[PDB]
Structure formats: structure tokens, C-alpha cells
Image: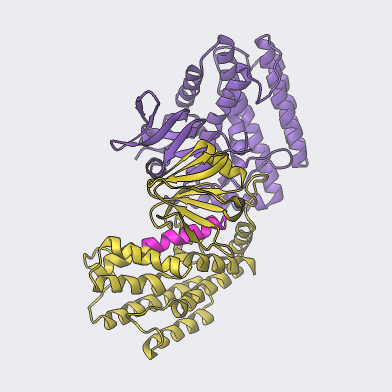
Chain colours: A purple, B yellow
Amino acid sequence: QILTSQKRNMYILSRCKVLVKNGQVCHLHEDGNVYTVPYANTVFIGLAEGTSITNEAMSMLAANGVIVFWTKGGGAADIICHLPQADYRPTKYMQNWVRLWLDEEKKLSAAKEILKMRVDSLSTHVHDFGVDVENKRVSSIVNKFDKGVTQATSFESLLGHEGTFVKSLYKEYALEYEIEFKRDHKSADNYNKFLTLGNYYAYGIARSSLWALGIDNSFPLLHGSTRRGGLVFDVADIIKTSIILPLAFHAADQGMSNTEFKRSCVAYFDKNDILAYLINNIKRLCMEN
Amino acid sequence: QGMQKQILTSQKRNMYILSRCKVLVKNGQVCHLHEDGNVYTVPYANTVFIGLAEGTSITNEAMSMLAANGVIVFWTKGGGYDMFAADIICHLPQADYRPTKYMQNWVRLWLDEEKKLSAAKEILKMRVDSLSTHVHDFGVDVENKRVSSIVNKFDKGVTQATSFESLLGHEGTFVKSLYKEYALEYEIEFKRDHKSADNYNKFLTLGNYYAYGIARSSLWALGIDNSFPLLHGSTRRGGLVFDVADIIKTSIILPLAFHAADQGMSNTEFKRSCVAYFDKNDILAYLINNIKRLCME
Ligand SMILES: [K+]
């Protein structure tokens, strides 16, 4: 009875057992401590190292539209993610997505639109610290990206401008914090670490938006190599450069803890209604044809 | 000392249902530790689907190692035919995200109204094939004259039909005529009705849900989205599940429900009889193979 986009909680759990105690979904730790999860008010649960989960907890989570995924996939994009399967989704959106996807020109047009959404999010979702997104250098980065997107004749061309856009923004944030930044997942520095961690939050909220509309992850708009993971990453990338990147670099520069950083992500998603934002934008991609 | 239940999916019995155990990594291998103390290894080469049923759990290490060996995990209620959580099944399990060839072909079929109608006629005829294949040692003899007249009437209507509307007409007549025959066989007055408290209607309602369950798994295993029905309305959530389940609702659910109601079974016993029939006669594989026939042609 709570709207999907109105759910405000989400979690990345480590070194604990997720189970049902006293009719509550909760996680139990080695010290005996039990912490509960508001199952009717939770967007997703991510499961990291040293975790386990029972079918009983899965049943309650799935019955309340909570998505569950594992941060280790066995291989970044190999994320194992379990969706609710018994509560049937709306049909209208996926039916329109299919017609959109099969039409190679409508698909290219949709791809350009979901790319430009990154620009819209960048100017809408701002922060009172770090990089001023309205300065001349970011304005130039945005313009070069927008014109390149407006003019491409192939998906492979779109990936070129997409790569340049993201990489240039990385360099601008690196300059702001006087660090030499190089994107690497294995890297132990807090900048890459908080980026990786924050991207799980972008993933989780993006899968949720897609599940809410019943649109399959197997129909991505941006394809080609390398561009693997499914539609969820096209959606998550909308807020990757606008929300996750500045939040991560801010946290890393202050020596913020993981707990505090994760809280800043959740707080920002709630304050700016990001889940509702993603859902509405995907739905408009889906219908206005 | 139960180890696993194997279910035939298509050509191989590569779906394992596990119950009352912890799935974990031991000695660099995925295993499941049971309450009795027994630990069993998971055969990667022979396993494609693992269903986690009642009293199960899994660690992040096991989940990770299973995925590395191309093993898909789903969560289900007891029996293994009531899945409530799983990922979507794509073309191949890791290196690419594209819909399965079955989903791709189903989509093409669904967008073409002339092919959609042809598919709708064939799934109705599958209902007839199930009626003669899946028989029972009790109740209605489906090979008597009265039932034969119902089938011939239904088959003639489906053949001559030129619209989905006409198909739905013959479909209704076929089902309620079977209701009448089973009511006549068990010598009872029966009007189909969800709001009734009698065991016959309750077992039909409950049994139909079991049929939706196994139909849901059949579509899922092929990576086919259930938002693309052939006969049920396009606005009907999970409409395709109901279309597939209708194949066995009159051949399996209907006689089992009337038999359970006649012998005064409990809800527990009734479900077990449905699940047992599903397992014994490989009903999941039956549905999967039929769905493949529809879109592969
Ligand atoms: K395998």
C-alpha cells in the first residue's frame, strides 16, 4: 500500500545473516545484535561478503516488491539480481518497449534521449559543494556531448561521445579536489571505492524503476562492445555523473566512513525523489510514440 | 534422507529443487548441508536451474560460485512449482544481455495479428491433446461418447473461427460442458463459482493457482515475458501465464479437484496430489515443449 517510488530505505549488507525473526525481516550479526529492515518501505537489499539469506526472508521481501542482488557476481556488470516473480507487472509499458526496441531507428532515437537525460539530471540534481556544474568548462563538456549525441548515425558513435562525456567529468572533479584520478575497481583509494559502492545504489534504484514498469533488463538501448549489463545501466548512468560522482568525491575527500557515505546517497535519493524521477523518465521514453 | 528433486525442463532434467538445507561453499565447491548432517556436492555440468524451496538459505560465496558455473538460482514455495523470486533468463548466462531466441520469436509472433491468431488456435488444440494424454484412474472417462462430442464441437469451432472473439466463445462452451460432465459423473449439482464454500469450487480455485504456478515456471525457463498473452486481454497482468495454464486446467486440475473433494482431502493432501502428478508426468517439460512449438516453428 506504499507506492514503489515512495519507499525510502535501501541497504548494502555485509558479514551477517538475513532472516525472519518475530515476523520481521532482519539481519543478525556475530555479536548477537539483530537489526530490522522495514520490508514495506525498502527499495532494495544488496548482499556483500559474508552474507546469507533464507527463503523465508526472500519470500517476504519479494511479496513487498523489494529487489535483492549480490555485489559479487562470480566474474561490475555480472551482478546477480533476484526480482519478484509472483506479483505480475503492468503490461502496457513492456509492450511499447518491444515495439520501440525492434525498430532500429526508434531505438536509436530512444538511445539519444536516454543519453540526454544525463544532461538534464546534471543540471537538476545539484550539490552545495565541489564542482560548479554551471561553470564554463562543464558547460563546454556538456555542449560537446549534446551535439555529438544529436548527430550520431550509429550506436557505436553514441558510445564514443558517452565515453568522452564521463571521462571528462572525472577529470574535472579530479581537478577540483587536487587529485590525479584514474578509474579502477581494484584500486583501494576511497575515490574509486566510494564510486563503486555508490554505483550499487544507482544500480539498485534503476532495477527497481524498471521492475515497477515491468520492463525487462534484456532490452538495453545502448549496446555494443563494451557496453554489457542490460538496460539497467542505461538508466543508472543518468544519475551516475550527477549524483554518485559528486557524492563519492566529496565523501572520499573528507575521509568519510562507508556508513556515512551510504547514508548520504539514501538521503539524497529521498530528498530529490530520484526513484520517481527515473520511473517518470523511462515511462515517457516508452509512451510518446 | 532427501537429497534433491529433479525436474525435466526440455531435453535434460537440469532443474534441481533443494529443501531444508544451507547452500554454501565447502572445499572450494558448492554444497548443500542438510538438517540431518548430510552434505551433498552440486554437479555443475548437470545443473542449469537450482530451485531453493522451504527451509533453505544460501551464502554470497555459493551464489557467486554457482553463477561462475552457469547455474541459475530461483526461490520457490514447497513442491518447486511456485517461484516468487528470480532473475530474468537471457540468451547466454553472462557475456551478453539480449532476450532469449524464444522471447524474440514470441515477440514477432505477438506483433503479427495473423500469426497471433494462428498461435491462439494451436494453444487451444493443445488443451485437447492434454485431455487425451493426461488421463486418470478415476472419475470421467474422457473417451466416452459425451466427452467426444464436446471435443469435436470445440475442435470444429476453433478451426472455423476467424477472430479471437469467436475463439473465446468456443473456449467457454468447452470448459463449462466439462464442468457439467464431471458434475454428472460425481452425481452432484455444480455451478462454477469462486464465492462458493463447497470443496469442489475451492479445490478448483486452489488447483488453478497451482496450474498458474507451473505455467509461470515454464515461461520463465524460456525467458519469455508473461505480458504477451494470446487469448487473455492484453491489459491482463501475467496474461500469458493464464493462457499456458489453460492447457492443463481441464485435463489435470479439474479431475484432481473433483477427486480430492469427493474423498474429502485436506488442502495439504490436495496440493501434494497436484505436485505428484506434475512430477510423475513431467508436466513442466510438457508445457515448455508446447510453448517452444508455438514460437519456434
Ligand atoms: K551448468
Outermost residue toward the bottom?
B145
Nearer-the-camera pick, A212 or B215: B215
Magenta highlight on residue B183: no
Nearer-the-camera pick, A125 or B39: B39
Nearer-the-camera pick, B174 or A49: A49
Could one spot residue B160 in this view of the protein?
A: yes
The quadrant the N terminus of chain B occupies is bottom left
Residue drawn at the location 49% of the way across and 33% of the way down: A46
**Position of A21 relative to B174 (above/below):** above
Residue range in magenta is B209-225
| Residue A219: image location, x then y, percent | 62, 47
Q: How many badges with numbers are in the image?
A: 0
Nearer-the-camera pick, B202 or B180: B202
Q: Is residue A200 left or right of residue A171?
A: left
**Position of B235 relative to A150 (above/below):** below
Residue drawn at the location 71% of the way across and 31% of the way down: A162
Could one spot residue A123 in this view of the protein?
A: no
| Residue A87: image location, x then y, percent | 42, 50
| Residue B213: image location, x then y, percent | 42, 59
| Residue A191: image location, x then y, percent | 62, 18
Q: Name the dominant secondary structure of the magenta segment.
A: helix
The quadrant the C terminus of chain B occupies is bottom right
**Position of B28 relative to A87 (above/below):** above
